[PDB]
Length: 198
Length: 198
Ligand SMILES: O=C(Nc1ccc(N2CCCC2=O)cc1)c1cnc(-c2ccccn2)nc1
Ligand SMILES: O=C(Nc1ccc(N2CCCC2=O)cc1)c1cnc(-c2ccccn2)nc1
Ligand SMILES: N[C@@H](CCC(=O)N[C@@H](CS)C(=O)NCC(=O)O)C(=O)O
Ligand SMILES: N[C@@H](CCC(=O)N[C@@H](CS)C(=O)NCC(=O)O)C(=O)O
Ligand SMILES: [Mg+2]
Image (cartoon, rainbow over all chains, first blue to last red):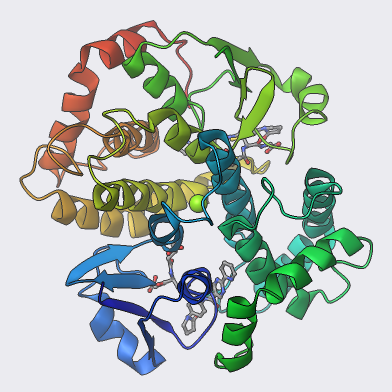
């Protein structure tokens, strides 16, 4: 297909889509807009949010909807219907956490202390739950890498920016990050992508 | 399999799963717990959250991951892979809004103010986007009912409790509600379920 992904110049909620394209060796236009471009683009989007993915003249939206679409019938999906559910549920558990952060929020009275509350008190419970869920296994679900592993690495990267001691009590969770980053297609993308904070 | 759904005695995040079981005429145990039971239940859960669905002794979590799993290979899924992506995208757009609300906020005055603000300043943009998306079509995606239509009815039922005039400018969204509510298996569940505020 002719794929055009639109997002800010940011990893953000588009990065999961970028990893999937890289891993699958799928070519695409990685369209990154400026903040001053946004207002006029927003009017044309179905629900006024990005990322959007244009597929052969058709517009898809919602990052995880698009990610699931792209990984259907690939080796990233989960090997049984039940394991597909586990993949979706890990992604949604991580997304629920990331979506609690006031990313847009201006007021840095609340924004900072809301961040620091989420990072100091809640992140460790999540980390302990992910660690326990992973146990001694190589990947989060099944016997091979899934896009949930990708999302863990993507989500944990942004979290480690603000709380660099996040994984100090969880070596097994660090190892999983490194495992993902070492997949040649992923490594290649990580090496050549725009360096951005978020 | 044998299914056991655990949630509070509330529609909440479990109701999408309960609609799907009703529509598919699948028997399940509807386990509803009290607050008092919460700490004991929680200790068993993978990520500290309900609903969970136990399936032949194995636990699934995340309401939307579970609903997707249950609708797979059914007429509620979306008739093609692109329609399935649209189903997912509409569901996540609804869920993103519902997740903004401070459901568990202890301070009543702060809770009511945030609800009122979200419903007054934010909801109308979503309702207009959904109306535009639906246009004159019968259902949100494709030519037959999907679990996206279910989730619209379920979400809009709870929002209308707090903002009765929510849909006064959008009769086509009311009509969609009525059509879901008129499906015989869903109508039966609606008539029979425990009556709870939320
Ligand atoms: O920074 C984000 N979003 C963002 C920033 C700014 C603004 N606007 C534009 C200019 C000023 C402003 O407030 C709007 C949205 C963000 C970045 N990563 C993630 C994210 C999600 C999931 C997983 C990982 N990462 N989520 C959100
Ligand atoms: O009221 C909700 N949740 C809720 C309340 C209370 C508590 N308890 C636990 C211990 C203390 C406490 O506060 C936990 C959860 C709720 C209700 N509807 C929805 C919801 C989401 C999506 C679609 C439809 N409906 N989401 C959440
Ligand atoms: N759950 C959606 C979130 C989409 C979303 O809210 N995106 C933000 C940027 S990270 C946005 O476009 N905001 C635009 C606005 O509200 O003006 C997804 O994952 O795609
Ligand atoms: N996105 C998740 C949310 C899970 C969640 O947080 N559920 C709430 C109940 S609505 C919970 O378990 N809360 C415990 C508490 O607030 O004390 C899902 O759809 O299942
Ligand atoms: Mg979500």
